[PDB]
Image (cartoon, coloured by chain):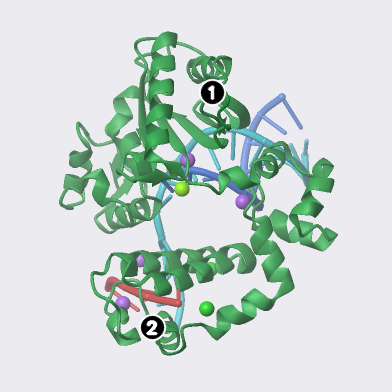
Chain colours: A green, B cyan, C blue, D red
Amino acid sequence: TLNGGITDMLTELANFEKNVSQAIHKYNAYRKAASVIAKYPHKIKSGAEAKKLPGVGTKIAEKIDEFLATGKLRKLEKIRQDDTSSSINFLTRVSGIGPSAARKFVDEGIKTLEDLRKNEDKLNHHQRIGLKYFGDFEKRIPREEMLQMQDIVLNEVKKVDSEYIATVCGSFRRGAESSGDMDVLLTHPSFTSESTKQPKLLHQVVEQLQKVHFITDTLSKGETKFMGVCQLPSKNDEKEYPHRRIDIRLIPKDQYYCGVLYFTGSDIFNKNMRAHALEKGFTINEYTIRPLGVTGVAGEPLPVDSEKDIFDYIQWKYREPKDRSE
DNA sequence: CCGACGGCGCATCAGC
DNA sequence: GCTGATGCGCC
DNA sequence: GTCGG
Ligand SMILES: [Cl-]
Ligand SMILES: [Cl-]
Ligand SMILES: [Cl-]
Ligand SMILES: [Cl-]
Ligand SMILES: [Mg+2]
Ligand SMILES: [Mg+2]
Ligand code: NA
Ligand code: NA
Ligand code: NA
Ligand code: NA
């Protein structure tokens, strides 16, 4: 982190744009700039130097000059002092409260953790769980703990059906020493792009993980995606482990490589790769890569037998997961 | 200058 | 009840 | 806010 000061500033700007201004393209622009600066291997000496990086433009270069000179950004100093902006930014830290809900809550006068706790009746199911575990959800998960969680999930899934394959993705698969949450990609030969030969494939797995008290709460659940809370078991006399977020995604078995590409991320990596695909005349989702016809309609799914095949289509050199942390 | 900016699952609500 | 919009979430 | 054409 040679340029941590700058990347922190840009991230705070991004969050303000997303949460307060509700400007999603500005949010993405700031994050893209922060990401490109974060991997730049020199300590940045000026705005002009930064402006040579793709995604850093005139306005960001100016902000960088201000920050290098003074160590702060007047724009941010003002935003921090603003009560409405401060409140909104805080409320969006609760899982389930977005920019819209946060602004609506602040209008009602609900703008602190204390206010939230006394107005549970005003929260939906997801938000009530987000509040319950507010503290826990902001803690990172050490890789050592991720390994214990992997063992529980993989062993429990095997007990449901030995044909399931579960893969931990996200930052874990990128080799991070700590993770924000646990991301699990699940496949079963009965669920392909052509047919669903068994019902409740995801349900059976969630149920089993609940039965062993690993999964503790549910935020949302459908046929292909579960979003919930889990917790490692603690030993006798041991303090409990924090509750953790868990996401499970059931992907058609024949579409594993596209699925694991998506779920490995990072998010900014996915955005960059998908944008590059479009420039190259292709569209990528978690299921397929398809050509874009002259008109605009996506064509038929192209053959994929490896993650690398996807990179080959868009003429990118292959990047191992560890090199996708953007 | 101006259009595009990644793609999608689940929850909630309005209209019919 | 369904369909489409919108919010919020995931990478 | 930035980029491409
Ligand atoms: Cl915007
Ligand atoms: Cl600052
Ligand atoms: Cl695939
Ligand atoms: Cl598809
Ligand atoms: Mg994750
Ligand atoms: Mg994430
Ligand atoms: Na630039
Ligand atoms: Na939130
Ligand atoms: Na996740
Ligand atoms: Na573009």
State which chain disc 2 sits on.
Answer: A
Give the mark toward the camera: 1 or 2: 1
Q: Give percent across and percent down for residue A174.
A: 30, 44
Q: Position of residue A60 (x, y in %)?
A: 42, 80
Image point 57% across, 44% down: which residue?
Answer: A137
Closer-to-camera residue (A236/A61): A236
Query: Mark 2 is on which residue type?
Result: Ala
Q: Is residue A219 above or below residue A202?
A: below
Identify the residue at horizontal 65%, vertical 50% (top origin): A94
Instruction: Compare marks 1 and 2 and give the one earlier in the sequence.
Output: 2
Crowding around mark 2 (Cα neighbors within 10 Å: few <14, some 14 to 19, many 20+) is: some
Please give the name of the residue rendered at 37% of the width and 54% of the height, measured from the top-left corner. A271
Task: Please give the residue where the numbered disc 2 appears in the rendered image.
Answer: A61
Question: Which amino acid type is marked by label 1?
Answer: Phe
Quadrant of the rendering where the N terminus of chain A is positioned: bottom left
Left or right for A201, reference A188: right
In depth, the one of A208 and A61 nearer the eye is A208
Q: Quadrant of residue A144?
A: top left
**The residue at label 2 has a CB less than 8 Å from ligand 7:** yes
Q: Secondary structure at mark 1?
A: loop
Residue at image mark 1:
A214
Give A194 or A232, whichever is nearer the viewer.
Answer: A232
Mark number displayed over residue A38: none
Q: Quadrant of the C terminus of chain A?
A: bottom left
Residue A258 visible in this rendered orientation of the protein: yes
Residue A90 vertical position relative to residue A197 in the rendered view, above or below = below
Tell me how far mark 1 sits from mark 2, CA to CA: 47 Å
